[PDB]
Amino acid sequence: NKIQQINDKELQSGILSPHQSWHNEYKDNAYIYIGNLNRELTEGDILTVFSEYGVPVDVILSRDENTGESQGFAYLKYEDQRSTILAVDNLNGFKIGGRALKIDHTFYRPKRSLQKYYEAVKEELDRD
RNA sequence: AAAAAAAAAAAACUAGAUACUAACACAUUUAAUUUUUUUUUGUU
């Protein structure tokens, strides 16, 4: 609802196409921070809603090291960037499980401690 | 024929009739800043 507020102003002025859009600030970014998730949505189900706008190559769900349950945020890289422009913009503020999730562009830095979780995820997304 | 040493209207209630006052106020108002509220939970 922070970002959703921008695009309405932006569009209203007829900004139209990325050169003048704030989405142009990125261009080298693909991963999207996916916030305010419900707790029971897992990687496969976050890999349901987000293929509407593109083809995901990677995904990471943030979850506590001990109990292994959702922190409530994920990082999902689309194959073709412009999906990011599309997902952030179009799907932000949308309800799943009662709570309206947040998306925004992100620069994502991998962490050693999950290293195996990368191949374990990749191998499934490497199937396609 | 005379001198008459100067004061009367109401009030209340309820409705109705009509003037009027106060340079009263009348389209601007939005670039620092508080309605910005949630069971904390956004990662070298």
Image: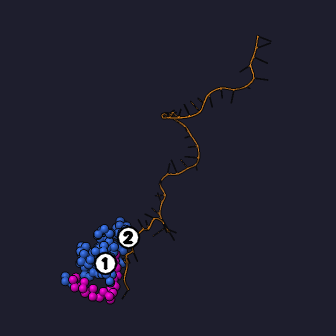
Q: Horizontal and vertical percent for residue A122? A: 24, 84
Amino acid on which disc 2 is placed: Lys
Q: Please state, as top left, top right, bottom left or bottom right, where the C terminus of chain A lies in the image.
A: bottom left
Q: Colour of chain A?
A: blue
Q: Horizontal and vertical percent for residue A1? A: 36, 69
What residue do we see at 28% from left, 74% from top?
A40
Q: Please say whether residue A99 is visible from this viewpoint.
A: yes
What residue do we see at 30% from left, 79% from top?
A69
Is label 1 or label 2 in front? 1
What residue do we see at 36% from left, 78% from top?
A25
Q: Horizontal and vertical percent for residue B2? A: 76, 14
Query: Is residue B17 left or right of A114 when viewed as pictured?
Result: right
Residue A72 lies in what quarter of the image? bottom left
Q: Nearer the viewer, residue A101 or A82?
A: A101
Q: Horizontal and vertical percent for residue B35? A: 45, 65
Query: Is residue B37 left or right of A79 when viewed as pictured?
Result: right
Asked if badge 1 and badge 2 are on a common chain, one would say yes
For mark 2, what is the residue? A2
What residue do we see at 33% from left, 78% from top?
A71
Q: Residue furthest front?
A: A67
Q: Is residue A85 above or below residue A66?
A: above
For mark 1, what is the residue? A70
State the extent of the magenta-drawn residues as a range.
A103-125
Q: Colour of chain B?
A: orange
Residue A28 lies in what quarter of the image? bottom left
For mark 1, does the 10 Å Cα neighbourhood hold few (<14), some (14 to 19), or many (20 or more) residues?
some
Which chain does the residue under circle 2 lie in? A
**Label 1 secondary element:** strand
Q: Please say whether residue A90 is visible from this viewpoint.
A: no
Which chain does the residue under circle 1 lie in? A
Residue A100 lies in what quarter of the image? bottom left
Amino acid on which disc 1 is placed: Ser
